């Protein structure tokens, strides 16, 4: 009751450090930090957020309910939150060199997938038709996915999605098939965005297609957010009606998302001779809130702001150029070493390596390379048969580049990857002429292989150890 | 790189602190912290997170992609993430004293509204019927809300919702109306959860009603999560099939959400005599991922974990008892002063004050009180004429209680609130027999009153300034 002692014990609790309260978690965090430090990060969706950003996530901004938008709030005392949110929005539009009279932005999305879902809610409405790249061809779940057996992605549950595909030769999106199919399916909205594609998108062509079908062109630039900001790859802003993005990945911020949308005259009705105006702002705004979300995560919005500020520095622009340089280096190196690079190469931060040119699959390689502290993700290539046996490894440069790695370094990486593949091959051949993934993992745990793995792992960790790990 | 130095300054940026990189944000955070410190926070959905929690939010856990669940990943190298997620789940089931064979919990929801949407996705499926308390009667948007014009809440867009009402004469939920209407509408899922109700729910009765209609009984304990943890209030776990919650509010963690669900026997099939098992785990799990969400917010999950650990301390249990004590104190004081308290009082952390007993509305009062550094939120009382003129103020104790306030302190607060109300009335009468809430705000900003308001504000701030403000 009174037990002031306890009440203090209580006041005390709330103020005692992480280290001291719940050590278990403190350790976990530190163990993970160590893991990040000693490993070679080639997962294209990963990056390391700056200290500034992390510092903002840890703020008291966590505490404040700010339902609604700046200047239309449903709670009081949002004067500082409003500075923040407005600042964030302003910085975002700056970072992408967008005219405030032609663009607005909502910065409340909790993450990427929330952002996309919000746009579909605002513009497509239930059962509305969406087309995105088929998942095995480098699409993302949120861009739609269903099998004959189940509607899998929420996009494909609450909307009718159909995929457009990448030509299993060229390795490029087959915009022509898209065109024909779009005329049959009548999409309400077409997504211009990938999770695994080495090439820029023909936005201008996509927009032709969309306008032809009276659909919206929504770009998901999550993967190339940062690349576009630094102008190292074409901007989708120039042709799309709406652009969604993640604030992490190449934008190197905390996990959150953003929706950019067109403001101004959509078209003039010669029938009325007057201008019909983009309504996207109210729809999207209403979709996010009070449609889908509740309380904004202000501590996340702060982190995004911090990220955006960094995005407009010259160091950032350089970083992005380097990111793409590194990717090219890595691609060239593997290609020289005889590996097949889907599409031939890369215009961006990732490549898709068709391990079939070495006679193995990403399914296996992923797991081995993992055991050697080389983090990548498997990923099907055009013309893959079973997605239980993906042919490909998706490799990207953002994470390592943020560590400092340059072209020569990326070449050394390509070599470490190669050793990884050799090991994979060894295991597979003892695995027997068509062993299961199961038997493969068992043999990998096998004593003979564990020795080879430990070898490579050590070299890999020491190499990674030599570069810093942003954010502390 | 060409400009090594520039590259060196790049590495620098990523590691240099917030205070130094982006002072603008730094100030904003500090100004907000100050705002929180000097104000009296009585917004029922607010609380102050412990430093430990905020520390975890700040961590590099932000960086890791861990799509999927522990031992069903889509990424390699989730070994520590897996510890964390599993740890979190373990702690969640502990904190709620749930039988792990009959309950599971998913801890990935980005926030509360995401959690609920995920449950409806898993169990209700599109256009499925949901019943929740009508919003102006103390429901939440995510429990459905739709007007003769427009489906507002995403719940009400993608599912068919119809509300059950609070008896305007008693201020209680009208469980009978529920019963009758449920048999007309046939809900697939019935929500047991409020955003503004002073009383416990008959989970008991609701379960009869749900079972009667073959519906699921989903409790949204967002507001009372902490109360339930400390057992200061009857638990929904005992009757509901699923329980969703926010990890802030009374749980005093960071902003995120969680979904508890039943595992085990649904019912012996007397027809067969074997066991019909609960499939809730896979449904909910699949809904959250890969249905609705992408990358888990691991840094948020960490924060939640830390919170849950604190929830299991005796200091926490004390805090909760105090929270309810404080609410009673505040309620009793106002009631004594002649103010009308919806339902007569409170079993929990909040009261709904019908300012009609003092001849005014929450619309006005909220703004006055705001200007005096007393945060609450306006709110309709059951049977208010129109949503445009809310008669009510929702007041809660969690935030201030976490600061240290006890019963006597809460009484002083009730008195400060009263002065607020007096000022409200003064302005209103000069606002005259008519006049918009706009005109009221203008008169309030008027020189005359700004003097009085600055007086009250100063007193209020000095009182608040005397208590600590959790988080470092
Ligand atoms: C009843 C209820 N449901 C859900 C929420 C979740 O809102 P948010 O997603 O901002 O945590 C709240 C708060 C609430 O009071
Ligand atoms: C193309 C694409 N869509 C959506 C997302 C969503 O990311 P998250 O799961 O953190 O929202 C990402 C990342 C992405 O790269």
Image (spheres, coloured by chain):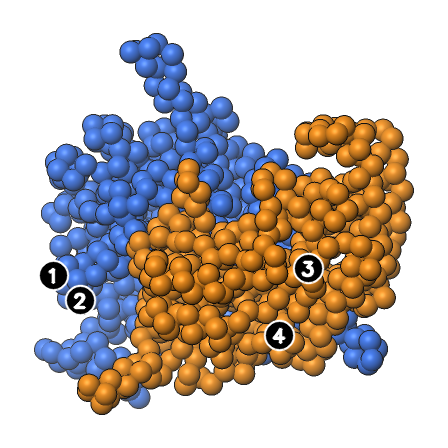
Chain colours: A orange, B blue
Quadrant (top left/top right/bottom left/bottom right) for the C terminus of chain B: bottom right
Residue drawn at (26%, 42%), measured in percent from left and top? B128
Q: Is residue B209 left or right of residue A195?
A: left
Give the residue number, with chain letter if any, for mark 3.
A351
Check residue A233 in the rendering and tell me which mark sits there, or answer none: 4
Give the residue number, with chain letter if any, for mark 1.
B385
Q: Is residue A64 left or right of residue A399?
A: left
- In this view, the residue in front, A315 or B472, is A315
Residue drawn at (55%, 50%), measured in percent from left and top? A136
Crowding at mark 1 (Cα within 10 Å: few <14, some 14-19, many 20+): few
Give the residue number, with chain letter if any, for mark 2.
B389
Measured from the top left, where is residue A108 in percent x and y?
A: 45, 65
- SS at mark 2? loop
Check residue A292 in the rendering and tell me which mark sits there, or answer none: none
Measured from the top left, where is residue B34 in percent x and y?
A: 52, 70
Which image quadrant is residue A339 in? bottom right
Callouts 1 and 4 in the same chain: no
- Label 2 resides on the chain identified as B
Mark 3 vs mark 1, foreground winner is: 3
Q: CA distance from mark 3 to mark 2?
A: 59 Å
Q: Is residue B296 left or right of residue A430?
A: left
Crowding at mark 2 (Cα within 10 Å: few <14, some 14-19, many 20+): some
- In this view, the residue in front, B401 or A218, is A218
Quadrant (top left/top right/bottom left/bottom right) for the N terminus of chain B: bottom right
Callouts 3 and 1 in the same chain: no
- SS at mark 1? loop
- Label 3 beta carbon within 8 A of ligand 2: no
Residue drawn at (47%, 65%), measured in percent from left and top? A176
Q: Is residue A409 visible?
A: yes
Q: Are marks 2 and 1 in contact (CB under 8 Å)?
A: yes
């Amino acid at each position: 009751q009174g037990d002031a002692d306890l009440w203090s014990s209580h006041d005390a609790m709330l103020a005692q450090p992480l280290k001291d309260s719940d050590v278990e978690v403190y350790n976990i965090i530190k163990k993970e930090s160590n893991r990040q430090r000693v490993g070679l990060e080639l997962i294209a969706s990963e990056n390391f957020a700056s200290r500034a950003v992390l510092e903002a996530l840890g703020s008291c901004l966590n505490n404040k309910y700010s339902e609604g938008y700046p200047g239309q709030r449903y709670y009081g005392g949002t004067e500082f939150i409003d500075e923040l949110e407005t600042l964030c929005q302003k910085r975002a539009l700056q970072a992408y060199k967008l005219d405030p009279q032609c663009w607005g932005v909502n910065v409340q999305p909790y993450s990427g997938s929330p952002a996309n879902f919000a746009v579909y809610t605002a513009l497509v409405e239930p059962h509305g038709r969406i087309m995105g790249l088929d998942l095995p061809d480098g699409g993302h779940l949120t861009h739609g996915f269903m099998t004959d057996k189940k509607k899998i992605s929420a996009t494909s549950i609450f909307f009718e999605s159909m995929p457009y595909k990448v030509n299993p030769d060229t390795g490029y999106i087959n915009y022509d098939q898209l065109e024909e199919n779009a005329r049959l399916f009548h999409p309400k909205l077409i997504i211009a965005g990938t999770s695994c594609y080495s090439r820029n998108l023909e936005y201008a062509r996509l927009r032709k297609i969309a306008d032809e079908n009276g659909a919206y062109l929504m770009a998901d630039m999550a993967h190339i957010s940062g690349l576009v900001a630094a102008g190292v790859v074409p901007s989708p802003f120039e042709h799309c009606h709406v652009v969604t993005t993640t604030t992490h990945k190449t934008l190197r911020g905390c996990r959150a998302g953003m929706i950019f949308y067109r403001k101004g005259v959509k078209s003039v009705d010669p029938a009325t001779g007057k201008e019909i105006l983009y309504n996207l702002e109210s729809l999207i705004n209403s979709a996010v809130f009070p449609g889908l979300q509740g309380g904004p995560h202000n501590h996340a919005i702060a982190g995004v702001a911090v990220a955006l500020k960094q995005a407009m520095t010259l160091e950032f622009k350089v970083y992005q150029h380097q990111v793409v340089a590194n990717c090219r280096a890595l691609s060239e190196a593997l290609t020289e070493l005889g590996y097949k690079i889907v599409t031939g190469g890369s215009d961006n931060h990732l490549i898709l390596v068709d391990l079939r040119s070495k006679g193995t699959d990403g399914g296996r390689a992923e797991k081995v390379l993992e055991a050697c502290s080389i983090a990548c993700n498997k990923n099907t290539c055009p013309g893959d048969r079973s997605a239980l046996r993906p042919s490909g490894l998706r490799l990207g440069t953002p994470a390592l580049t943020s560590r400092g790695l340059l072209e020569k370094d990326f070449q050394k990486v390509a070599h470490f990857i190669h050793r990884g593949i050799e090991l994979t091959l060894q295991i597979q051949s003892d695995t027997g002429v068509a062993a299961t993934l199961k038997e493969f993992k068992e043999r990998l745990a096998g004593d003979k292989y564990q020795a080879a793995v430990q070898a490579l792992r050590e070299e890999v960790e020491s190499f990674a150890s030599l570069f810093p790990l942003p954010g502390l």
